[PDB]
Image (spheres, coloured by chain):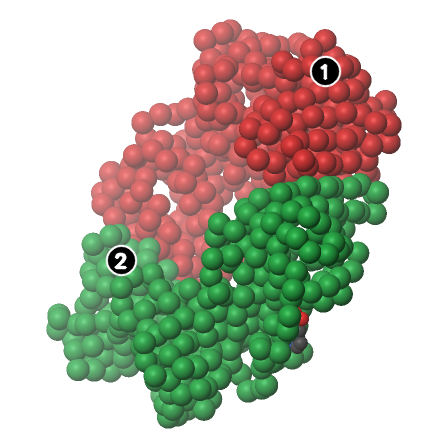
Chain colours: A red, B green
Amino acid sequence: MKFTVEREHLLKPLQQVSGPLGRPTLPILGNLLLQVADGTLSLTGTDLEMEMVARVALVQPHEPGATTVPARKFFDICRGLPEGAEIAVQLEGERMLVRSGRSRFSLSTLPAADFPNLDDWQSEVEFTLPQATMKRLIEATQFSMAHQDVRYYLNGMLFETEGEELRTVATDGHRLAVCSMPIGQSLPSHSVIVPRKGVIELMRMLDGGDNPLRVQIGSNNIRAHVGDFIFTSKLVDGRFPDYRRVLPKNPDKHLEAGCDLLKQAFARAAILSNEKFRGVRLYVSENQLKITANNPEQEEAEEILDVTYSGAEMEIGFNVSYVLDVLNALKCENVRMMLTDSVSSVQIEDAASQSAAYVVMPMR
Amino acid sequence: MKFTVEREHLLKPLQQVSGPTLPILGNLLLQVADGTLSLTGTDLEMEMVARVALVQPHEPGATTVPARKFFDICRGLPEGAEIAVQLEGERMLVRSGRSRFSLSTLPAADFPNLDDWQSEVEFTLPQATMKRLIEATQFSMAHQDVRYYLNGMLFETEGEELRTVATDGHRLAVCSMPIGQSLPSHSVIVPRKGVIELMRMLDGGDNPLRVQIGSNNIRAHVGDFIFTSKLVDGRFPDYRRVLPKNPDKHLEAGCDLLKQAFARAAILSNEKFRGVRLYVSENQLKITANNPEQEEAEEILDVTYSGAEMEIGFNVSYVLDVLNALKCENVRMMLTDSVSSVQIEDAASQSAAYVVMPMRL
Ligand SMILES: O=[N+]([O-])c1ccc2[nH]ccc2c1
Ligand SMILES: [Ca+2]
């Protein structure tokens, strides 16, 4: 195995395939698989749950073969070499020699044949969409995912195909985000759970260009192709809860207000909320919202804002972090809060589009 | 106590005074007197006093409030906001637009004041010079060493120069700058936390700093801020005895090439104690590293060197720290032998000097 590649054709690929890898439980898991074959260097990183594969074309002399070497050491070497460096690599038994200028690096190898390999699987649904759509879908809901919950499925993100739409759902038990976006193709109905780390990789591989995303989904896997990267993840086995089941029945009490005015008042109020419980109270009345927080020292914050509202007056408490998370993920001009009563969750949406909705439970 | 003041005029004062365990140490002392608002923060070891002018109706008085909360509130208000503040028994009410806040207070009397003391040594210098002096040597301070007197920086006055020296027993940094004033010869040790805070009040503009040094205290005045720190009470080593007495072997090298070769080679050094071996020979330097994996790095660099060949190891971070402090075209390394420390300087300046012990590999 031999190749010589210019630094910058190696770097971005090396970073992408390092993404699944911290502290490797076993040595081979900290390695990348390098393969030269029919004119192409493939780089593969895995954590056993997912794989990221990069392909780099080789325009300079090369010879086939395969080995594995430490991912971070090799990345840091290529990164630290000077701009435009030629990186000449050759497998030499138990070492892989890397040379560039008068820099020389000897990396210890482990057999390519020992590198872990995701099992072959079959595609069942396929579609293409813009990267901006996939980014939109993920950033809309990602924050609502659970973090290291014993209920393993909540640590992921639900991906769901219905009619002409791709949808994401995330929840942690206390709050929910769902976001549907259309993609100009009719589709079958699959409902799959992507693991937290896969959602991060998916996001990581969107460059913000005009290469579209090809998605493939099987019973137990998901694959995304962007440009010269192929990301494949095992799917999480479980039942994600049902979003239709938890949206509010009849929240015909509608408050409309500026997203940023609301965010900043909630932000200011939160400063004097309970440090642990983060509760604030909202008083709604004709065209007016009042937000108050207090903490056990009897410090108090009050914010008054003009809003659009015709309903009966009411009063309700929310965890201000959850509201702020929602308003931060909204990044729109106006928000719609759809209330029922002081003991019922609120549904929050961009006032100008129902493509996303958020459910937050009330607190006493 | 009541004042109404532009959010605009409180931001930078609050940022400065929220820099310096006990509960009232997390509070700010606010004082209105003679048409001025004074804000003070402290950690008992140092303090920062900021002053704001008050043109709008105001009432004299004083109290203390949670520093981070008062800061986050004022900062959280919208740009252009007016902030009306009034003391009201055991609470301070803050108001702006239709936002209202009541913060808990502690009595202004209970707020600690650093004991009064007397100035013995005084001088003015540009902010820029003080920043250069601190930047040159800051990284060589000890962090949490039993030898308390290394956990900080020597400020020395000699001739018409201010000098800083810092060291952790393994590497040492010295920098001197002329301030155009005849000074008595005098040495004090500023605690590192004090050095860090002094640096953060230096915005890098045109503005002289005024320094006042007491037997146990240092004070700096710039603009509308007054920073005061206690000194550290011990015996700082003498940089003159640390400089190698005749480092006869002199090598010059490109700063950045040296740095990148050090940084790259270190990738394959020991993760816990990162060191590289240097083999100096006729106009050539080779840097090598090894690790328990039996992995090896080698960099060869063109350098300027004639004189006896030798192999000597160095700690990577000590050298990198020096080369980053230097940020110049070429560095000179003045070597003695394989067992002795080395002196490093900017090849085109003696303003600063670094001494680094060798590492056995
Ligand atoms: O680098 N040195 O050789 C060095 C640094 C600090 C020191 N303090 C006392 C001796 C000494 C030496
Ligand atoms: Ca109010």
Q: Which residue is rendered at x = 16% and y = 78% of the image?
A: B35
Chain holding disc 1: A
The foreground one among B58 and B202 is B202
| Residue A336 badge | none
Task: Measuring from the top left, give residue B327's x and y in whole percent.
Answer: 48, 53
The foreground one among B143 and B282 is B282
Near mark 1 (Cα within 10 A), the count class, few <14, some 14-19 or many ≥20, is many
Task: Tell me the quadrant of ligand 1.
Answer: bottom right
Chain holding disc 2: B
Q: Which amino acid does label 2 sit on?
A: Ser
* B188 horizontally vs A238: left or right: left
Task: Measuring from the top left, give residue B234's x and y in whole percent.
Answer: 58, 86
Disc 1 designates what residue?
A: A62
Quarter of the figure that contains the N terminus of chain A? top right
The foreground one among B75 and A179 is B75
Near mark 2 (Cα within 10 A), the count class, few <14, some 14-19 or many ≥20, is many
* B281 horizontally vs B134: left or right: right
Instruction: Write down the quadrant of residue B219 in the picture.
Output: bottom left
> In what element is the residue under mark 2?
strand
Instruction: Write down the quadrant of residue B115 in the picture.
Output: bottom left
> In what element is the residue under mark 1?
loop
On screen, B260 above or below B118?
above
Task: Measuring from the top left, give residue B232's x and y in whole percent.
Answer: 53, 83
* A303 horizontally vs B359: left or right: left
Q: What residue type is labelled 1?
A: His
Task: Measuring from the top left, give residue B76's x and y in whole percent.
Answer: 33, 55
Instruction: Write down the quadrant of residue B14 in the picture.
Output: bottom left
Q: Which residue is rendered at x = 55% and y = 72% of the image?
A: B166
Disc 2 designates what residue?
A: B99
Q: Would you say the residues marked 2 and 1 are in contact, meaning their CB atoms lie under 8 Å apart?
A: no
Q: Is mark 2 within 8 Å of ligand 2?
A: yes
Q: Which residue is rendered at x = 78% and y = 41% of the image?
A: B296
